Image: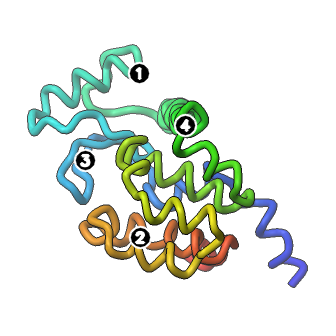
Amino acid sequence: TTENLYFQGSMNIFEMLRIDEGLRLKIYKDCEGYYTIGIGHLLTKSPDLNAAKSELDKAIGRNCNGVITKDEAEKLFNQDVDAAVRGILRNAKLKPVYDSLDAVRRCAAINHVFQMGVTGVAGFTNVLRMLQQKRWDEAAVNLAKSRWYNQCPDRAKRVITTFRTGTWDAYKNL
């Protein structure tokens, strides 16, 4: 479809993570129980809500009282995406795999690091080798064994499908 052919140009890392993480203007606990706000911004792993609000005020730069605006959520979101990209490119293990990937799977790579962090992703020794060798089906099967996926499948299922196919299909028809 001419509409189907345009959907590609509408999808990017920002729209991808926006779907996987949602958009919340108030502090909430994610599927792992950690305090979160905005578009998947983990505030802290501490169970103390007071620590979550203290980190929020530091990140936004004002007395937020646990609430932020949509424009603030986007600014924080852009910083987190940049941090995940920079984390990949300076890492001697992730950068060669990332460089080998196509544009769409590169988005899935940034997404993965955004969710898990650099050392967590860099620990997927076998998945990283499979991806560099273009063994897409095997990579997706091994990702489906991870604790990252199995503890919170809805946040990870679309990333795994994107690693398998290199298309945006899993983000169609929400």
Q: Which residue is mark 1?
A: 60
Tag nearer the camera, 1 or 4: 4
Task: Work out whether mark 4 precedes mark 3 in sequence or the reverse, and give the earlier one.
Answer: 3
Q: Give percent across and percent down for residue 11.
A: 70, 60
- Residue located 44% across and 79% down the image: 141
Judging depth in this view, the residue of 110 and 92 nearest the camera is 92
Using the image, tell me which numbered label, if any, was put on residue 143. 2
Q: Amino acid at mark 4?
A: Ala
Q: Amino acid at mark 3?
A: Tyr
Marks 1 and 2, how far apart in space?
A: 34 Å
Judging depth in this view, the residue of 111 and 54 nearest the camera is 111
Q: Which residue is mark 3?
A: 28
Task: Work out whether mark 1 precedes mark 3 in sequence or the reverse, and give the earlier one.
Answer: 3
Marks 2 and 3, how far apart in space?
A: 27 Å
User: Does residue 132 appear left or right of residue 63 in this picture?
Assistant: right
Q: Give percent across and percent down for residue 112.
A: 47, 54
The residue carrying pointer 4 sits among few (fewer than 14), some (14 to 19) or many (20 or more) residues within 10 Å by Cα, namely few
Tag nearer the camera, 4 or 3: 4
Q: Which residue is mark 4?
A: 92
Task: Work out whether mark 2 precedes mark 3 in sequence or the reverse, and give the earlier one.
Answer: 3
User: Does residue 19 appear left or right of residue 33 in this picture?
Assistant: right
Of helix, strand and loop, which one carries label 3? Answer: strand
- Residue located 60% across and 79% down the image: 173
Split into 4 quadrants, where in the image is the C terminus? bottom right
Using the image, tell me which numbered label, if any, was put on residue 146. none
Split into 4 quadrants, where in the image is the N terminus? bottom right
Task: Work out whether mark 1 precedes mark 4 in sequence or the reverse, and give the earlier one.
Answer: 1
